[PDB]
Length: 126
Length: 126
Length: 126
Ligand SMILES: C[C@@H](NS(=O)(=O)CCCOCn1ccc(=O)[nH]c1=O)c1cccc(OC2CCCC2)c1
Ligand SMILES: C[C@@H](NS(=O)(=O)CCCOCn1ccc(=O)[nH]c1=O)c1cccc(OC2CCCC2)c1
Ligand SMILES: C[C@@H](NS(=O)(=O)CCCOCn1ccc(=O)[nH]c1=O)c1cccc(OC2CCCC2)c1
Ligand SMILES: [Zn+2]
Ligand SMILES: [Zn+2]
Ligand SMILES: [Zn+2]
Image: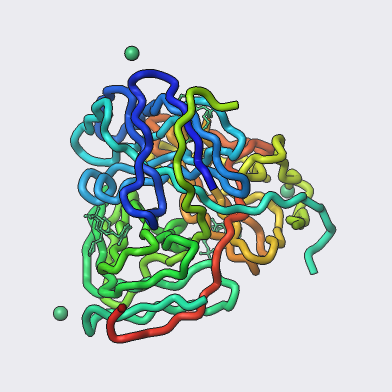
């Protein structure tokens, strides 16, 4: 039960989790972005991750950004085997622009347990 | 495998799950709210919950409210150890205002199994 | 560990998963739809599914559609015991209409592990 990660640049921040039983690790922006009202942005973390076996990585919303600034997270399904730069798709549904600065926490990364079933076609179920 | 909860006021409704194999328990509004088009509201349940070990509580959308009224749920990650009042962040993307009355079902609470990995930094993955 | 499915019409496409460790099976539209800017549509797959025991089926967003076209997935909680036609609720938050053609991939289906706890009311937690 290790989540490993590597920094892809000097702008990356190591993910953090304050509480031992918090659902997610904090993801941090590696760059500044300005997100206009009713617009989206793909926000780079400049980290790559190796998820534990038996899960995928869900990029999930921060609670305060959602309730206070009408920020949501799009996309969000990081496959267990993905080794690229982790991106966060932010949706700004508010009426004001939303500013992201390098080092800001912008999402959380949850290790969601899943099955990897084989698929079988039948003519009709039970 | 118990989900425990306590009512924080007399306005709270005990969560329900009709089917034994439904993914979620129904969450009910403790108050009336009017949510304008393209607006958000934090809706109180006036319950506190104690989630089973090995999960977090995902506040997830009701299917009919989403398809019929363009209601979505923001935020939604309830940490395993959270003991406060459970809030539901509703996003109204429709063109008409959305009315919540006390006692209305407004979301579902899913006990999502997750890992709680330790984090380790390396220079580069494999 | 089988995911079974049946086609409800000749327009359905068998779900696919390219990578062995991809989080989701691709869901395909059985029909053409035009989704106006800032509108929603319930998109039929014309498949029925039988999920493995111990999960629900999460209809989750495709990453490219989210980042490139501002498409999101609403609703999305398919109960373990659901045997109806699988619908995908697409939200088009972009400024242009979004075209779905029969056979297009429109979402992914994730077998999310969950608990099915019994619920217990107490006066106050710990
Ligand atoms: C344009 C589009 N390309 S994409 O090929 O559709 C997905 C590429 C990234 O896959 C991993 N992933 C999946 C979901 C997620 O939320 N975050 C994330 O990092 C995309 C979508 C989402 C995130 C992206 O992040 C970019 C930042 C640097 C590399 C990718 C890109
Ligand atoms: C303003 C902001 N404060 S916040 O500190 O960011 C989060 C406080 C609540 O944390 C638990 N939680 C987390 C996610 C969720 O969806 N629901 C929920 O109850 C917030 C965000 C979401 C729900 C909230 O509910 C309030 C209702 C009464 C107490 C908190 C508050
Ligand atoms: C109108 C509304 N009816 S509903 O009764 O609220 C839900 C009916 C479908 O339940 C399974 N389900 C649940 C969530 C999901 O995302 N997809 C899905 O197939 C609804 C909501 C979502 C999907 C729907 O799909 C329709 C396509 C053909 C049958 C249902 C319908
Ligand atoms: Zn630089
Ligand atoms: Zn009162
Ligand atoms: Zn036909």
